[PDB]
Image (cartoon, rainbow over all chains, first blue to last red):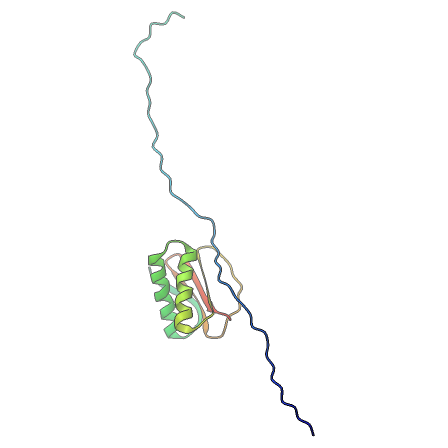
Length: 46
Length: 86
């Protein structure tokens, strides 16, 4: 005959943002040098 | 660039908006993580959280989504997966 009223509640939760990324690239530039440290005719005496 | 939708379980309005949002994201950002972030954030605002977005040229996925909130499409050679879950 005794009806008791009760109130229930569950705990809340917490989320968080995040990200993923594959490997990254970057540019590059090269110029080949053309040095010619060469004389005309060295008179050798080997 | 040209948008091609391959799969969708999504209303026509969200489909077109997803493309438009991804299109702007791809114009604005070069890095996939930032492209995804733009697309995700815009959807949470317009269509309520919680959306997730994956952007890339090479991947496989296995995900669980809410009904009527999933699309997979290309912009050129870049695939975009967008869905709601949570």
